[PDB]
Image 1 (cartoon, helix red, strand yellow):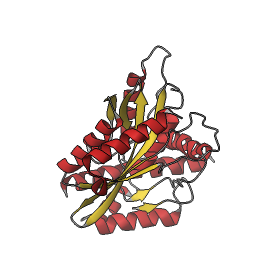
Image 2 (cartoon, chains in turn yellow, cyan; image 1 turned 180 degrees about the vertical axis):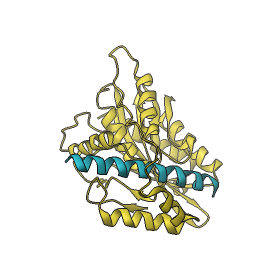
Image 3 (cartoon, helix red, strand yellow; image 1 turned 120 degrees about the horizontal axis):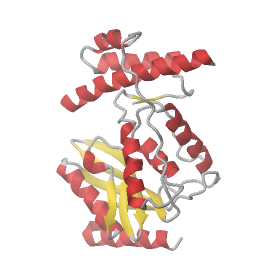
Amino acid sequence: FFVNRGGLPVDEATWERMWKHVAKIHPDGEKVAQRIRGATDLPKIPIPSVPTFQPSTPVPERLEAVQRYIRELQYNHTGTQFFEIKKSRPLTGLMDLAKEMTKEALPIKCLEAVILGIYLTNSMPTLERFPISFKTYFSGNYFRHIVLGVNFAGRYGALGMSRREDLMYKPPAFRTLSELVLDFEAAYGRCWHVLKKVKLGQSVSHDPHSVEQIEWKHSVLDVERLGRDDFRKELERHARDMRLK
Amino acid sequence: KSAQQELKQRQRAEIYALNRVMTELEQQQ
């Protein structure tokens, strides 16, 4: 998973590196490059339209539309991340990045989807947004994932992008934050991953010009050292911390 | 300017063809 630095269009070096990565990863890799590179019969991809909402549309319907747009961008399986995301940047820089993502319309992954969800829900002041990071373990390897937890009318859901359907979108129907996180943990266990750490952030400002930073790791929960009851207690403590601004 | 738009269009089309190929590969193996 290389990261494209230098913006779009992809520079010659990053383009060649992406194609070399493809040639080594994919069997038929250089045949793949030979078929695709320079081809004149490739499909035209329509630029997906950014959803806009009537004031009468309920927020959960808007969330469905936003998740649909994010999915339409497609999950990035090319091995080259096309947008560099510096997580410590001020909000307004990340929002400019999300706007450029909407204008250039390329495949994305976990963190790009989180930033896009923040950018696309800034118009919903009754909706709170906060990042949720997962660190899991499988077959001697550690894995990291992130979604945008969401809160509306006292119920929790999520937006995001993931390889698996049960590791991204959750409609805002979970009555407590712990139930949402435990649903994610159940999906992880279903795909034979052990959940090690959960990192929950504070609410993100709805001001796209804000210079504040996203507070990614307001609560870092070691699942195994906490146990069930203390895990739930800490998740509810984070929920309280959030709803008290 | 206008040539850079054609550049971005060609690159995006190739990126999505490649992404389809790699998505099929990954969903298999």
